[PDB]
Image (spheres, coloured by chain):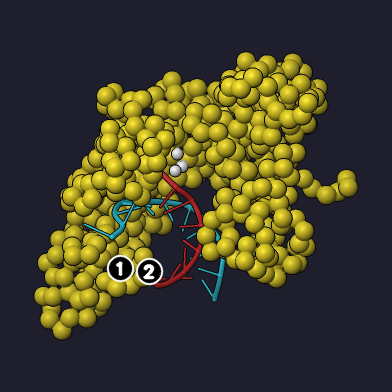
Chain colours: A yellow, B cyan, C red
Amino acid sequence: GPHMATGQDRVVALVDMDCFFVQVEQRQNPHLRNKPCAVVQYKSWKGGGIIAVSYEARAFGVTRSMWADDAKKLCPDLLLAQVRESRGKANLTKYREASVEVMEIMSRFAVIERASIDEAYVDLTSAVQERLQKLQGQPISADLLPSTYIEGLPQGPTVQKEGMRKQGLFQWLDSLQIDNLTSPDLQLTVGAVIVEEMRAAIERETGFQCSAGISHNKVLAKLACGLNKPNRQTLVSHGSVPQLFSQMPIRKIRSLGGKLGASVIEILGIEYMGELTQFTESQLQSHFGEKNGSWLYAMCRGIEHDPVKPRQLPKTIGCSKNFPGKTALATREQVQWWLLQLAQELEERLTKDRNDNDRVATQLVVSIRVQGDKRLSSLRRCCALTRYDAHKMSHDAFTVIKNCNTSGIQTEWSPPLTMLFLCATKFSAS
DNA sequence: ATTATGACGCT
DNA sequence: AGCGTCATG
Ligand SMILES: [Mg+2]
Ligand SMILES: [Mg+2]
Ligand SMILES: [Mg+2]
């Protein structure tokens, strides 16, 4: 009744750049614009591995994690851009720099949480209150929402996509109560107006297009963002949740696309998120633990409390390279050379980070994988990071991992290493 | 022979 | 601390 909380206290947006690395390459090279194109890492093995795909290329079935040679079988005219290689490894600096450009624009509208290289959550609650105060009870025109979809509409008693979008928006706006400054639906709508403005600013000032979701929490905003891509935004209201979730596979909700989600499905014998409502909070906690159970109980009703953290910068700065199959490192010279390459890239990135962001990392994490281990990381060990010096950092990493060499010989390394990873962590202001 | 990251939970 | 899970450009 009146005391059952409904999780409608915040306005949260998730902004996600469309096919991000592709857009960075298309800005730089106009010949790639409005073409089926993909971004690849490396080239010798099967043409390189695709990591980002333009929407034109997706129409042919090209996806991430596909080898370029196979993508070319699906789309012979596919255009490819290669990630830069420095010190023998992929170097993602261009995309990190482009990400900073976008995150700085977003931060003008509200405090953001950098969730990944190309996506950020936005807490718009206060900005919405402000814009509502300025509105003075004036209604929201559909002209202010030119790329917004309202999930679940139109409904009830034209065969073109834009026409359907507009009918849904008109139904939504007609049902809006514009005088209640505390109406959650009105707050979401104003949030969407703000996000239209933020997305327009990103495109004007960078050239990059993005999609966005607007809802009452991070999980719904992320889900909403995915409903209409690319270059569109979607409002998921609290009221839209029962219908949306009634046919939503559990794996589509963030955090449930892996083992936990598969166990929800198998243990409870359900398929869709809405089916979770039939279980008590204690039942869900008994199966999935106290934290997961309470989270599932609320989430399946559209309610989630995780805050938008005020954090625009990554918490760690890392450098990683796999040495698959026959390229695995089997000599101490090899291991030292690659640790040095990784450490030199890490030093460059850390020095730039210290100048830009007034902080210093204090912990170096070294991770390796040995040949034949199913896990992605075979061993992880930390040591002190007291100086931004690549030779020191690589020597320290070698000292930390050298007891892993099973070889009786000091020159050989066995079993050979299939992955090296150096990560700087535990930043302190300076 | 996917790869290169990056966040966060568990114990 | 070191490990596992989830994401997924
Ligand atoms: Mg994206
Ligand atoms: Mg993203
Ligand atoms: Mg993606």
A127 sits left or right of A77 in the view: right
- Which chain does tag 1 point to? A
Q: If the picture is divided into quarters, which one holds ligand 3?
A: top left
A341 sits left or right of A191 in the view: left
Give the class, few, some or many, for how many residues have Cα within 10 Å of label 1's Cα (few <14, many ≥20): many
Res A104 → quadrant: top left
Nearer to the camera, A410 or A264: A264
Residues at discs 1 and 2 both on one chain: yes
Residue at (21% x, 52% y) in the render: A45
- Disc 1 is placed on an element classified as strand
Tell me residue A256's x, y (percent).
57, 56
Tell me residue B10's x, y (percent).
56, 70
Residue at (66% x, 34% y) in the render: A151
Res A165 → quadrant: top right
Q: Amino acid at mark 1?
A: Arg
A302 sits left or right of A4 in the view: left
- The residue where tag 2 is placed is A375
Q: Amino acid at mark 2?
A: Arg
Depicted A309 relative to depicted A157: above or below: below
Label disc, if present, on residue A284 of the rendered structure: none
- The residue where tag 1 is placed is A369
User: Tag count in the figure?
Assistant: 2
Give the class, few, some or many, for how many residues have Cα within 10 Å of label 2's Cα (few <14, many ≥20): few
Q: Earlier in the sequence, mark 1 or mark 2?
A: 1
Measure how far apart labels 1 and 2 are at the Cα level. 8 Å
Please say whether residue A125 is visible from this viewpoint: no
